Image (cartoon, coloured by chain):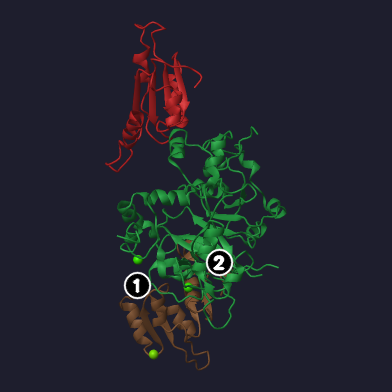
């Protein structure tokens, strides 16, 4: 989140005004809460699961401009997290198909599975 | 005699006995005459490569996609193949079966399937779109997606990952039509994954499995719906035997004795009582647009069809495979059909409609 | 099925590649003592997995009347083939008597095989 908020809210862009909503099932520790207090007007957090469509309804995913899926690039099993992030794309496209999803894949064949999704 | 009925209640079927109005040497079948049977083949005789499967035209066939491995538990595919080889079908009326999956898992299982006529094997992957184009997946009568890895994965998030990905992969292919109309049945483990199988339905995690759309249209089937069979078997012990005749193609306990002894379906020589075994009925569907009762679909009554088909052809009728948008105002292109079981006598009959029925073997 | 065996000994074995060696020479050697005549010996047939018997056969391979049927003790067909009704003793052992950690079904195979012959 720190590296994301550095590259996203950088002053070298124009006067951006999008808000950043986060969605994670694990509750944040005290350092993440201090980071969200450092960005009190630009960043909101909401604890939930992206697979559960009630939590997608909570973050207003139907009116969001885009949805971003960060990956754990140092995971122990790359096919496992590629499977999990593919499941996240399936869930968001199951709720709202007309959204723009940006994601990260760790192999190329798991990227090839994403084009088979009907949305 | 005992009458097996279908009604909404138990005091309704109390009126089933409260009525007076007063007061030639070849082995074409098994040793019992219940299934078809052929010579025990070698596994190379049924393995096709992708070019060989591309050459053989397969229409009206069944494609069984399998996500197997060396380490996964055995599914027991004989219980899938055996109801599709029952002797109340003619040999031309059988459906070809092609298994698309890893050849290692099929090697572990083929010694039970190797006495059936029209079985093929393509050693590939269900997610590979090339192999599904080779087996002509647009022309199949059913595509069945199973997984043997339904018990050894400990993630509880992506147990049904492969089956959902394969379902959406077939749902997004295109031919020279789109692959959203291919009839797919996928088996699930966690019933909460049933929301990912369809796009246009309104998903909800608190709806039960029986009320969801892709279950009601008969495209999903989890084993959790068979939990009611324990109480069903206790209250009437003949129900489970009625099911196993209806479902496994008439598995009488003579074959249970045979598999207790030899654990192998053995062929037999044709006797006239063996041919008397073939008089089981067959469940089938009926198109309401060209047949002998095609005129009745002008908003008629379903019970008129019931009495007419039972008088003429001696064929029962469970219910209606009604289109999902056949009751809507605007004409859509959704070819998804849901299931109505035992409609009343005065039920209206849309012309574009399918009828669940039990057909005799003449 | 062709070889008629009467008054013989059928040794059913629930073995594997990984299970520990039973030491079947100590079972065969008292049945090959020289105070029996060669016609008074009892034929011995091992019904089990051929892998486990492959691990053990280099100690048994100098005895006269030993046979091996590579099958399963629970399979009723193999027990009918070795004429289990005519044997003088049927011995049910298991090499998996030390590596199972369930403490509920250690003797599952032996009890099932005993009831299978009993029915
Ligand atoms: Ca009811
Ligand atoms: Ca859905
Ligand atoms: Mg705000």
Determine which of the numbered discs, if any, sits on residue C88 in the image: none
**Chain that is green in the image:** B
> Chain coloured brown: which letter?
A
Residue furthest right as drawn: B55
Q: Say if B136 sits above or below B43 in the image.
A: below
Residue A72 in sight from this viewpoint: no
Could you tell whether A95 is left or right of B230 in the image?
right
Image spot of residue A114 (x, y percent): 56, 69
Badge 2 is on which residue?
Answer: B354
Q: Quadrant of the C terminus of chain C?
A: top left
Crowding near the residue tagged with mark 2, few <14, some 14–19, many ≥20 C-alpha atoms within 10 Å: many
Q: Residue at x 58, y 33 (%)?
A: B269
Residue B141 lies, in percent from the top left, at 60, 59
Circle 2 chain: B
Q: Quadrant of residue B268?
A: top right
- Horizontal placement of B239 versus B198: left or right? left
């Amino acid at each position: 989140v720190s590296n994301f908020l550095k590259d996203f809210l950088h002053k070298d862009r124009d006067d951006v005004n999008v808000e950043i909503v986060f969605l994670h099932n694990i509750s944040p520790n005290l350092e993440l809460e201090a980071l969200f207090k450092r960005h009190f007007t630009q960043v909101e957090f909401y604890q939930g699961s992206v697979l559960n469509p009630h939590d997608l309804a909570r973050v207003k995913i139907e009116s969001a401009d885009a949805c971003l899926i960060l990956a754990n690039k140092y995971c122990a099993d790359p096919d496992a997290e590629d499977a999990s992030n593919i499941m996240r794309v399936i869930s968001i496209k199951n709720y709202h198909p007309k959204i723009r999803i940006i994601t990260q894949m760790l192999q190329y064949h798991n990227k090839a599975h994403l084009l088979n999704i009907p949305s | 005699t005992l009458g097996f009925f279908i009604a909404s209640d138990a005091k309704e079927v109390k009126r089933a006995f409260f009525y007076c109005k007063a007061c030639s040497n070849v082995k074409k079948y098994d040793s019992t005459g219940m299934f078809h049977w052929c010579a025990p083949k070698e596994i190379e005789k049924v393995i096709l490569t992708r070019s060989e499967a591309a050459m053989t035209v397969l229409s009206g066939h069944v494609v069984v996609c399998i996500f197997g491995d060396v380490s996964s538990a055995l599914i027991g595919l004989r219980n899938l193949v055996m109801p599709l080889r029952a002797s109340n079908f003619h040999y031309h009326e059988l459906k070809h079966i092609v298994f698309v999956g890893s050849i290692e898992y099929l090697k572990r299982e083929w010694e039970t399937l190797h006495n059936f006529p029209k079985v093929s094997i393509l050693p590939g992957t269900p997610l590979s779109r090339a192999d599904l184009r080779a087996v002509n997946i647009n022309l199949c009568d059913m595509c069945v997606i199973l997984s043997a890895n339904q018990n050894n994965i400990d993630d509880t998030s992506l147990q049904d990952k492969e089956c959902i990905l394969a379902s959406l992969n077939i749902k997004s292919m295109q031919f020279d039509t789109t692959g959203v109309n291919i009839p797919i049945i996928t088996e699930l483990v966690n019933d909460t994954n049933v929301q990912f199988l369809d796009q246009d339905d309104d998903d909800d995690p608190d709806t039960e499995l029986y009320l969801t759309q892709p279950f009601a249209c008969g495209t999903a089937f989890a084993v959790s719906v068979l939990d009611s069979l324990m109480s069903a078997t206790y209250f009437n012990d003949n129900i489970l035997t009625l099911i196993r005749t209806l479902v496994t193609g008439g598995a009488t306990p003579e074959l249970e004795a045979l598999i207790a002894e030899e654990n192998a379906l053995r062929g037999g020589y044709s006797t006239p009582q063996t041919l008397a075994n073939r008089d089981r009925c067959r469940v089938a569907q009926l198109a309401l647009l060209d047949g002998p009762f095609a005129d009745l679909g002008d908003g008629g009554c379903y019970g008129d069809l019931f009495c007419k088909a039972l008088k003429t052809y001696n064929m029962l009728c469970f219910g209606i495979y009604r289109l999902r948008d056949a009751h809507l105002s605007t004409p859509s292109q959704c070819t998804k059909r849901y299931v109505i079981t035992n409609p009343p006598y005065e039920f209206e009959l849309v012309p574009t409609d399918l009828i669940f029925c039990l057909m005799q073997f003449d």
